[PDB]
Length: 474
Image 1: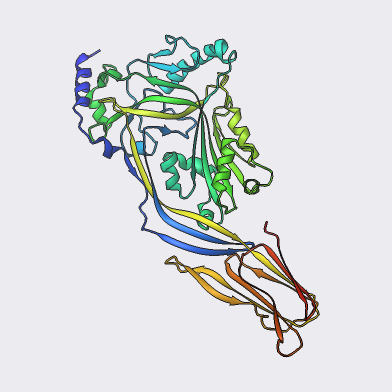
Image 2 (image 1 turned 60 degrees about the horizontal axis):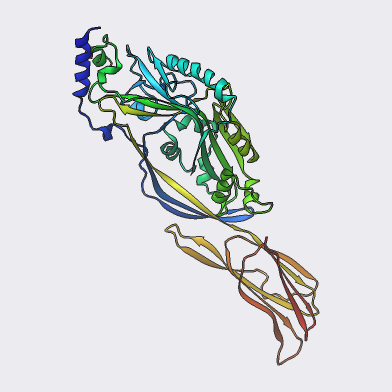
């Protein structure tokens, strides 16, 4: 080989000066500052909506991969540092490449056989070498022993698609396509959506550090071949220094409860909490549907998109949990170091998103039973809560349109009361039929708690009226 060509290439790369942080900075969406407080009425409940500005920013050397069959993502590959790397759509610098040895971490292997030497690094060559050793490890230790996988849990509330790609990588968009996340329904304040990512790592494959940038090419590669491909200081080289292989699950939790503890119940499901027969957690969990994308779940190297109830969550967690080398698994994350100095490439990703949090107030009924031997009058008032879009509480006075009207037994009515009713007050008086005290208050309460039904029953006589206030808050 022509030593002088490999000498020039090597100096060409060591001479590259560039700002690492600017090349790896990815900014998503800028949005004008926001704040809304919107009450919305629904058939059985009144919902208070909040919408604010937040931003998610992550410094990440770990690149997650959705891609089932990408040939560019093998350990030791050379990727170009440009805008397509930021989107996990890397330009592959495919030239004549020097041999490389990898180190693989699997249980109960001699560390000499933890090394795999490849003549010509390519996705075809490394998987071919890794599979050769997985087959031997499987018979001596895989089928023979019980090896757990390394599990990892990341969760986040779904608010925007750009916000999800900051959390889960720019490639998340494809996986998001399948999960049929609908943010319109989240912004409408009606639904709450969590996204869960599950990794089960079977093994990692890594390369030693590179002592000279020229060490990765054969002597045939020339500086002009690199310049021919647009390689320069503005557009420099990086190499994949480790790849995690295994199985992973992207999972959507979609529900219509607006409860405080939707997050707590969702957390409880992920932790494996044996949730209790009539919590509110179980009420919302039995109104939650689950969509899941599964990568590398079975001997078939492919992607499964499934729909089901939350009972499906325990079973998806568990099938990949144990690693025999029956299945090689697929690349689930990888790391890149600069060729020039082996510094790890760390991406600074950020975006603005509209955060929508939500409150619910259930609607109530007020039942009135008048079976008394007297004319009775009801005085029922309340306030209905609304928000000026500045954002403060506004109370508007309301009254029952039958207030002050003489009522006789047997009277029965039901007054529906929306979830925005505040300060319910109720006064019942009855005619005694004699001067000096003609009306006699039978019942008077202020600021009654908004409750699902309330039954106020009056009976008895003009001189001896009785009252019953019955409540059943569920």
